[PDB]
Image (cartoon, grey):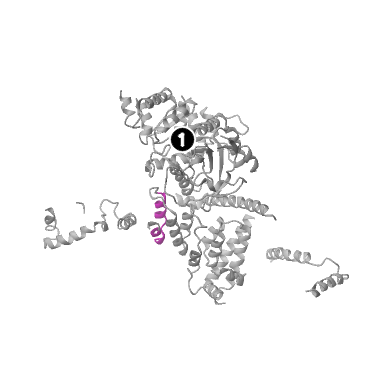
Amino acid sequence: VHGNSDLYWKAQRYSLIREFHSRPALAPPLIIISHVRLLIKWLRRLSKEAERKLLTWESVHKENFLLAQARDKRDSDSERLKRT
Amino acid sequence: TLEEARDRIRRYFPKGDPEVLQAQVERIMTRKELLTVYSSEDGSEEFETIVLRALVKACDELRLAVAWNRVDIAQSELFRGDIQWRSFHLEASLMDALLNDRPEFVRLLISHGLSLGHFLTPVRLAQLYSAVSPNSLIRNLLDQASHAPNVGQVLRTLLQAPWSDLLIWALLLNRAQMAIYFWEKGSNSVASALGACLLLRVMARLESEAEEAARRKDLAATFESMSVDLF
Amino acid sequence: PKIFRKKVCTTFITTEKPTDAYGDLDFTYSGRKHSNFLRLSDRTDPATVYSLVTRSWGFRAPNLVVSVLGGSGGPVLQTWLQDLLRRGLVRAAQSTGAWIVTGGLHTGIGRHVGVAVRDHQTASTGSSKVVAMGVAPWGVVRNRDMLINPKGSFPARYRWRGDPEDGVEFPLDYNYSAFFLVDDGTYGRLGGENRFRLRFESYVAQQKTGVGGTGIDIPVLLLLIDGDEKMLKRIEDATQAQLPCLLVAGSGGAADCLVETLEEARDRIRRYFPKGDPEVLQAQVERIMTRKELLTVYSSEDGSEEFETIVLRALVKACDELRLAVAWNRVDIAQSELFRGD
């Protein structure tokens, strides 16, 4: 079970980090300050050109990935045997 | 049809009733358009090209190539530069290639040059979501979406580049080769492979038939490995 | 990237003014990349044109430039020449690495070349494309009005309404990689383009292949198909500036010089192929016959095959061939040239 426990731990490692990033950063002996502040708020109730440059960069690498996939399938031995 | 010697011909082939049968054969010669000859051919070969020759003589042939599920006919009819295939011929044959499950015709007809922003009218997009077997899963999802075209609500209860509309179309009807081709043509590829993997696994848990749920889990594994390799 | 190419290139209407029409160019079709176009003056240098293509648009330096001329078959060309332009020209342009320079418009032999490029791009998966370029006069463009905004770096949505083919305006073809649009200022007629065309061909022919340099001069060849009377001045203006040429059988507009190189029956030949102006055109054809060295024949060949050996035959007739074998990245040519013990 050692390999499946590594695969499970890495996937859970994202949501554990996200839990600490989403916490009110004040220690639990002194955390009453942040709970008072959230109680007050409860009482009262990229740029476009940067995304275009990013997505065209992604599409360049997509095309190189698909061309190398087609060359690897074409130079395989079974498709040489089909073409002969 | 190669052409009184008429009365001669009606008196050594049939051997009886010359002038009545001559009136019959001349009735056939009134419509000599609808008559073909199979003489100087290969013999027991290339029957299909002569069927197309008879149907074009009696006159759409690209739509016949889709309907017979035979690709070499359509390919040879596109290399012939005398015809100069226009837009509405290619658009009609592409709808026949999408309603049926023929992905190699979709690849061949898009590579020839065709506008898809002019193609996907909302009438045609309404026709694609009605190519549904009535005892499937997407039929119940669309009917419950209208009970309270409406594919955005179907995505909500589950979750000019129009390539993403055809990707969502091919995922909801579980077409494997269609959805992979529409992934390879559109942009924003890493997020769309993870979105395809999510949507297929949600619909695979909700599937009644066991073979179709097995089919959807195999396709979702394919989209996961493509996002891994691209990233 | 758009402002300096607006200012350096100019257009004249004659007041010579900065440009407004350049950038990318998409069509209605899907799955394809963008083509580059530029509204350029007629009296401008090809030096900044070459630097604009090979450094800003993005293109490798050519190893070969072949210009396609003709166009006597308007609606339908023969299937024989259709197979020659499909196989023999484009597979050598894709293997050796080359530019095809034709008129960018639909008319003439522009459609037949562009269909050959698209059919080569569809019938195989070559993982690349054949760089075909086009020059066209600005006044003959069908709807040039979709190109006018002087800002720059934009896909201009070019449109085909499906119009009947009038002989005043012509639409651009959709199978080329880049377009040159020359603002001559007459707005009426094909013919005011060929000066910049021949100057740009000779400017490419003057430069050389290589990494930093130290290579052969890029061989520029001319490919003649049927054509009209308006090409005989172009054949002579080309062969005056030291450019080789090649001739296919085709029809009579090239068979004029084919028969005259196989050899008054002269005045006869000048009065059934062209059908007009005997003695002036006879003076032109005899100007071509002064330099019969720079003329080759493609008649009794395989057809759509062994194009590259005939290119070497034309360049050696006009005379290094081992260096051409290195520059084209093709090994069988050099190997066969080393086994020849002569």
- Please name whichever residue, B192 or B81, is drawn nearer the observer in this view of the structure: B81
Q: Residue furthest front?
A: C14
Q: Secondary structure at mark 1?
A: loop
The correct choice, above or below, for C32 with respect to C84 in the image is below
Within the magenta stretch, is there residue C28?
no
The correct choice, above or below, for C232 with respect to C129 in the image is above
Is residue C134 visible to us here?
A: no
Within the magenta stretch, is there residue B64?
yes
Q: Residue furthest bottom?
A: B147
Q: Is residue B152 left or right of residue C261?
A: right
Q: Is residue C159 left or right of residue C4?
A: left
Is residue C297 visible to us here?
A: yes
Which chain is indicated by disc 1?
C
- Please name whichever residue, C324 or C188, is drawn nearer the observer in this view of the structure: C188
Q: Position of residue B199 (x, y in %)?
A: 60, 67
Stretch of the chain drawn in magenta? B63-79
Q: Position of residue C335 (x, y in %)?
A: 50, 32
- Quadrant into which the N terminus of chain C falls: top right
Q: Position of residue B121 (x, y in %)?
A: 50, 62
Crowding near the residue tagged with mark 1, few <14, some 14–19, many ≥20 C-alpha atoms within 10 Å: few
Prevailing secondary structure class for the magenta stretch in the rendered image: helix
Q: Which residue is mark 1?
A: C191
The correct choice, above or below, for B189 with respect to B138 in the image is above
Q: Residue furthest right?
A: A29
User: Which quadrant of the figure has residue B48?
Assistant: bottom left
What residue type is disc 1 on? Answer: Gly
Q: Position of residue C14 (x, y in %)?
A: 56, 34
User: Which quadrant of the figure has residue C58?
Assistant: top right
